[PDB]
Image 1 (spheres, one colour):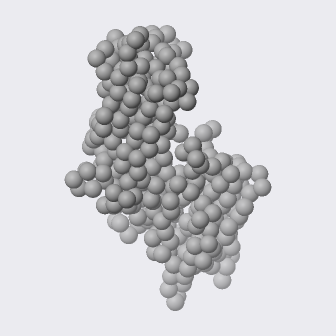
Image 2: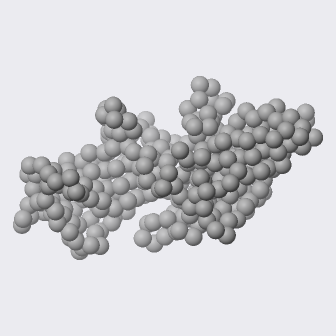
Image 3: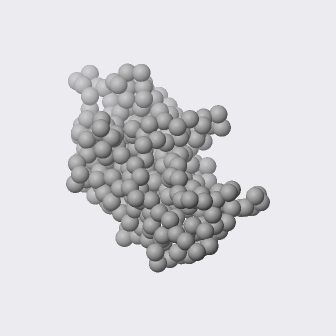
Length: 322
């Protein structure tokens, strides 16, 4: 009748997020049909990372086909919905506002934490059998980093507390909450039937955000040949939802900057440059720029403002390290 399923979360190391809340939603095929088997919400007194978390034993109903959804650091706004979930596809329809997990300064509220999700499919367990299922969970947000970079042959650059600013256009905080992983075979799979999770499309101008982020500190720096040098310095970070850009690419991310220091006695900026291409630098032999068609969850989009003699050149890369 019953079986024991041990879920062991994996990262495969030091920058992995602390977990305050855990939720295990198990679905299984019964003779009568698909039914919710387990919905368990565990609250951790000592927040720990996915590697520090011991395998979680779940008492399940033996089935030839079981689907497990794991949710870490769920926003308080979805707990009422999650506690009352009954259907798997109604879960896939659940949307959340990223603005919930963010404070006044635009950074994650440490107390609720970074929401993470993962889905694993096609689990077979027989009565009284014990199985360990190893799975990955990914962050339910994307990050847009903005850097100022001093380059060889360029001018002395920097930012000033009062006037240097950066404005990001067409970002959104409207996202589908649960999303499967490539690592668990529940994303970018051959047949869409083995995939889990929806991604936002044709976002309204109402849902597209714009936010200015004036510098707090002041520092100037010139290009250095030395190894200890930090020529590429971070100015600001923005959080955006995972979504597909429209066909016309009218909602593509845009950036503008003001009073970026250029030379000893001048400044320079950007006025609405669209981020039309991104270079995925995930492997040393992967330096190819591609069209920016999708904002993808658990990826950091790093926009760099390269300061030359005459002005700024914006270059954007895709990284998976937070």
